[PDB]
Amino acid sequence: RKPPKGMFLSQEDVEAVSANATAATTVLRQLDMELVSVKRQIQNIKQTNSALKEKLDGGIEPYRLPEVIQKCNARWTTEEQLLAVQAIRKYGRDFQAISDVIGNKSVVQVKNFFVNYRRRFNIDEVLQEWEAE
Amino acid sequence: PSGVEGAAFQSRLPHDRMTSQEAACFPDIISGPQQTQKVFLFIRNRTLQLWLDNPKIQLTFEATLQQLEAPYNSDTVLVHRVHSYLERHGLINFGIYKRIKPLPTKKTGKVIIIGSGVSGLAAARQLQSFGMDVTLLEARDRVGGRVATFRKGNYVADLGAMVVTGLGGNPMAVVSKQVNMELAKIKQKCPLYEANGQAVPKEKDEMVEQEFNRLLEATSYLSHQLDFNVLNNKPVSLGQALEVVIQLQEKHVKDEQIEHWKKIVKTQEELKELLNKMVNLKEKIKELHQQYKEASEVKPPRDITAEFLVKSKHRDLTALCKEYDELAETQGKLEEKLQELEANPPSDVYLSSRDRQILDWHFANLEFANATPLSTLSLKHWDQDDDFEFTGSHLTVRNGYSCVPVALAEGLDIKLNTAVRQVRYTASGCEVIAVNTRSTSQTFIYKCDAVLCTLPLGVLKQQPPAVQFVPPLPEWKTSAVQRMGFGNLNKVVLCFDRVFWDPSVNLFGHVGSTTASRGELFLFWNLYKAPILLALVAGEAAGIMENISDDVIVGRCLAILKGIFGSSAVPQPKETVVSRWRADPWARGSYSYVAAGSSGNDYDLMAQPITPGPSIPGAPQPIPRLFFAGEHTIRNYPATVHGALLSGLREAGRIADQFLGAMYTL
Amino acid sequence: XXXXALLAAX
Ligand SMILES: Cc1cc2nc3c(=O)[nH]c(=O)nc-3n(C[C@H](O)[C@H](O)[C@H](O)COP(=O)(O)OP(=O)(O)OC[C@H]3O[C@@H](n4cnc5c(N)ncnc54)[C@H](O)[C@@H]3O)c2cc1C
Ligand code: NA
Ligand code: NA
């Protein structure tokens, strides 16, 4: 009812190899062909990848910037407000970005800002202008 | 088993059922109450037991009833019927027993038996035992037929039958109690030496042996679970099946390699896209960084758009940098995944050359046990005798197997050097025409009530005919004869003056260089006490080596032997002998095999006796005149001495029922 | 523990 384990006998396969006098050596040459061509492609892409890895030599280390550690403050300076408006103009609704720019405000403080000052900063307008981009 | 059930098992009978044969003789009993069936059955098994427990003397009915116990010894006619059936069909009082009741004063009927092979001798002895005039005609100058034992001095070596294939249910058991046979176990351990002379490493011996066995199982599965028996209007052979199974294994291996290397390209290409992504990102980071530097360039005090510019560029750079770093993590993971796949590649091949060659030696072992190229065996039926194989270790005969035919021939009217030329069988009797083999001008004519033909299937197969039948055998018999397979196998006896091999090793192999020569001198035996090695030739190689001179052949032998044992340790054989069984005109081959296109049903056809048409027309149907025995005629035990023996017992029983009448059936 | 029986076709 079941073939020996490690013995692979499929119906499809037996009819495919019995059909002819040398359908056997045909299938087994096509597979050798498939094999050599796949191995060749591996060579190609191993090479391609070797080149790309060569380009990335140097990491991004010369370009990394140290991290500002400013503690979150609750008071909005005039400055911080202005930063914030421009931040909205450039980033729209990406609050996290905005918080990172201002550097001493949290995301929720940023949302609060959105609402409190909506009247006075014409935040609506600002936002639609960001959306045009 | 043990007890009376032991006896029944040993008599190749089911201890708890009546057989078809028994049904035939005792239809009253088997269509009756299960009780009397059990009585019957005990009477049977017990009588069997008694015979078996001491087969050196005739078991008379009186003795039997004497040792029967009640209630079983009440119905004495049941006992008599039973005993008689047993004696008749050679379940008891067969072989070489001391006769209590000395033979019948006058004989009834006349039987001429062609061939004093083992089957011949058997039937003859039984028929005589029954009080019939029996004469055997034998073409050779010796008894035994395909039991052929070489002797010179103390050197003794069979070129014919060599092995008792187990004593569990073997009649040869009874014989060996009756004859002095030095039986010797065979140590089934067999080292293999590669054509060079180096032993095959245990690792290899085992990986290969195991793969062999799996391939066989495979074919069986193709056969029986898949009905792959017929391929293109032509029946499949074991050999073809094997080759297909193998081709699929190689196919599967290439498939595995293709799937693996494709996983490697899939991943490698992932890495490619990631790498691209990372390079473009790095370039953006270079550019952006430049821009941020240019913005910190502007010294304070600066207005708020300027300040926003620095802050925003900074936020963006920290962003892109973060992203690049994640990508680089991913790159690490992919690279190590690729090192894993490049690390666990599936198996390079299915079989190396050393591989396929050792495998070829296992195939040659198969070709040898069947005496034929695996390309000729029936896929569906080659193994069909396997269900009846005996139990216990296979054994050799140290004094030679000849002793048995010889033993049997005692008391028998045997005409040697008498080659039967033609058989004539008619409504009224038979005449056999034979010649002297020495002077084939001299002629003999033998007249008889029936002929027992135990001509080898090879002989019967001959074209043009070595023996002529008048009238001709009916198409159904001749077709059966054509359909069967009569195969071929040969031996080389090597007699040296001192043992130069491992004396604890009964047997050892040699692996052939080619697939084609896989059967040439593939195996060797030391079974004799004396220094004698036996080199075996089977498969396609069997037939071909027969056209090569003795000398060349012992040459290829000592060659192999020197390769394995060193040129300075192997000496010229004092005596050498080489079988050529297909060439022998009395054998015309070694033994039958289920040819592809044949079935075990053909063996049954072979055993069907022939009934001549009436002499006068509109005259009643006549009694059968021609009967067949021998190894080719026994379905469950073909190509064996015990099979020959059994077929002999059979036909003698049938013949005797015919001409003497069966008193035990009322 | 030998593979094939010894002289059976099996
Ligand atoms: C090499 C070899 C090894 C074997 N090893 C084994 C083994 O190890 N174990 C086992 O169980 N079996 C073995 N066998 C087979 C076994 O020996 C046979 O099955 C058995 O001997 C067959 O007996 P038989 O009585 O049917 O035929 P045979 O023994 O052949 O007897 C028939 C007789 O007919 C004679 N004859 C032929 N033509 C004529 C003619 N025109 N006129 C008159 N007489 C004629 C023959 O010469 C012969 O004597 C082996 C066979 C061979 C060839
Ligand atoms: Na015979
Ligand atoms: Na093969």
Image: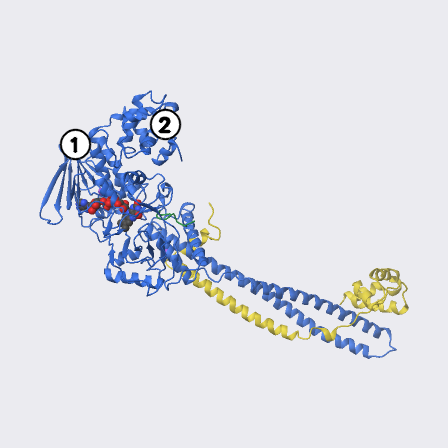
Chain colours: A yellow, B blue, C green
Question: For residue B632, which quarter of the picture?
Answer: top left
- B18 left or right, relative to B146: right
Residue at coordinates 33% horizontally, 61% vertically from top-left? B561
Q: Chain of mark 1?
A: B
- B459 left or right, relative to B597: left
| Residue labelled with disc 2 | B42
Question: For residue B71, which quarter of the picture?
Answer: top left
Residues at marks 1 and 2 on the same chain:
yes
Q: Find residue B472 and report its horizontal and vertical position in percent.
A: 18, 42
- B284 left or right, relative to B157: right
Q: Find residue B191 and report its horizontal and vertical position in percent.
A: 39, 56
Relative to B55, does residue C3 appear above or below in the rendering? Answer: below
Q: Which mark is residue B109?
A: 1
Asked whether B354 or B145 is in front, the reply is B145
Q: Find residue B467 and report its horizontal and vertical position in percent.
A: 17, 45
For label 1, the crowd category at 10 Å Cα-Cα, with few meaning under 14, some 14 to 19 and many 20 or more, is some
Secondary structure under badge 2? helix
Residue at coordinates 37% horizontally, 45% vertically from top-left? B393
What whole-number distance in Å separates the C-alpha atoms at marks 1 and 2? Answer: 34 Å
Question: For residue B301, which quarter of the picture?
Answer: bottom right
Relative to B334, does residue B370 appear above or below in the rendering? Answer: above
Amino acid found under the numbered disc labelled 1:
Gly
Q: Chain of mark 2?
A: B
- A52 left or right, relative to A4: right
Q: Is residue B476 visible?
A: no
Pointer 1 or 2: first along the chain = 2
Q: Is mark 2 within 8 Å of ligand 1?
A: no
Residue at coordinates 25% horizontally, 57% vertically from top-left? B576
Q: Is residue A11 visible?
A: yes
Amino acid found under the numbered disc labelled 2:
Phe
For label 2, the crowd category at 10 Å Cα-Cα, with few meaning under 14, some 14 to 19 and many 20 or more, is some
Q: Find residue B277 and report its horizontal and vertical position in percent.
A: 66, 69
